[PDB]
Length: 213
Length: 213
Length: 200
Image (cartoon, rainbow over all chains, first blue to last red; front, side, top):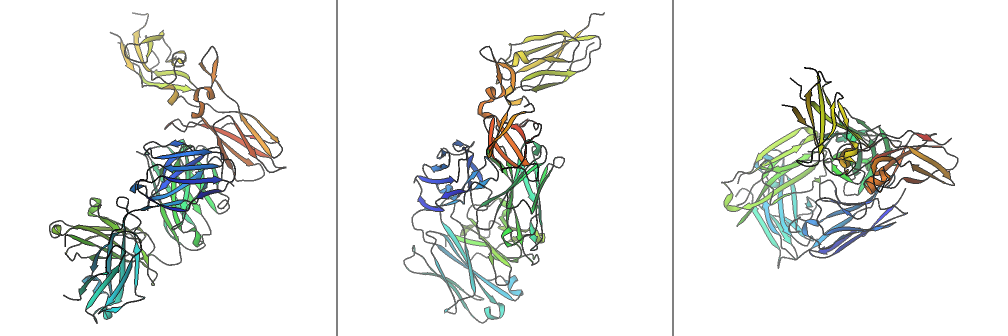
């Protein structure tokens, strides 16, 4: 088949920067090369078709160029909502072949997280488990450390966290960490806390609650 | 109004077959070429094949030629995809796409196929109660379900700004857990009602949980 | 006592355009008019008993214009005229693409050149009829389907010209069929398939 090599695999650029993504085919594809944009959890959306044509409704900052084996997608002035993974597609002959994609990350100023802590619900406690949740909201860059503490003791091995993809409007991230304990263990301690360390914070921030209070 | 709706997603045992359908409305599929495109978790787009409903011609990527069948029923205006002898690498979101011969102009929402020997399990939904500063956070914890995915909306979709629904985490138990939160003015607590609408299709679970301080 | 014409429909393939309607006349005749605006009306079929009127000569003057037609009913030569407006018709966007025909499929070396016959239309310019390709230009695409007569799985390719140059395995016979498509349309997008041609 015709191999499509897309470069780079990822890039980081600031709002307003010019961005260039390229795709090279192993042989002449006669301009049957399209560019699609895919945002988190959505189907891909056409941007450019037949190498250089802008699809209806697509912002003019997106453009395509190229012919033969070499193609380029350009974003003249990057906007926050352009955070996405971009893919080229060869469709002039079967099998149709997608490039491996280029993830575009948005660089922005530091933003400290806002921290919240939630106790397990009484309903869940009726079962034999307690989930304590800590939220780090709208921060940047992504690097962040969550340290759980139970009666001031450092926890390890009993938590899991997940992070959202960059926000399409402010380019920040949010993170959720869940500490899981059996109800028996939960009831043996009073103070539950999550200590957060991030570049935007002069010193670590701790949010906590006392079981029962 | 054009629409592509896929169904048939969910659990498939290793060695089993996925059998999906793509119901089209607002146009006749015989006027276009209908394609299947898949995407493994965190990976790139992969072309599977196309069917021309004008005469039933089907083209398969060589990787799927001997293990898949794409078909179409003009009277039901529906296209189908069956893939056999599934392995872990076949776990992916499968999309149906309408091809105009210049580009894909419409896509289905995508349906996840999870290749696994485990059984389905519905989630329990617990509130993440607001503590009550200037901004307050609240949410819902959707715990212990399998397989993915789960969808969450707030106030039947009316409330979307400030909402962060996190990527699920696979627990040691083999079940997923996910949290969804939203930040709102503290002065709205007790005045504005907040309800998270949770849906887990594999277990036919639909829950609306009111979150109060 | 005349019957207003009804079910006025446009039947058009490769620009050959005819307006059809009902009913079969009973003691009455019809006159069909065409225009591109309001007051551009021209009668083309006068007092006919036919239930169709060929309007090709008019629409080919400009295939991208939108045409309106009206059919008048008049009492026959034995013993206020009623009329009805037809649907709008824009030739370039609505004429049906006729079945394509493969002109040749010569194999030279490891490649087969599949040439599509260009089809002449009634649309003319500079005292010469235009081909379908002439009229549509790059708006027209040909889809090729090809396969080894000695196997199942089909392959495909597209071109915005009239030929395909494809690689084939030596000593193998392939079959070919082509189909025309106008990507920019939303309805009447494709022609039916050309007759299948096979090597040997």
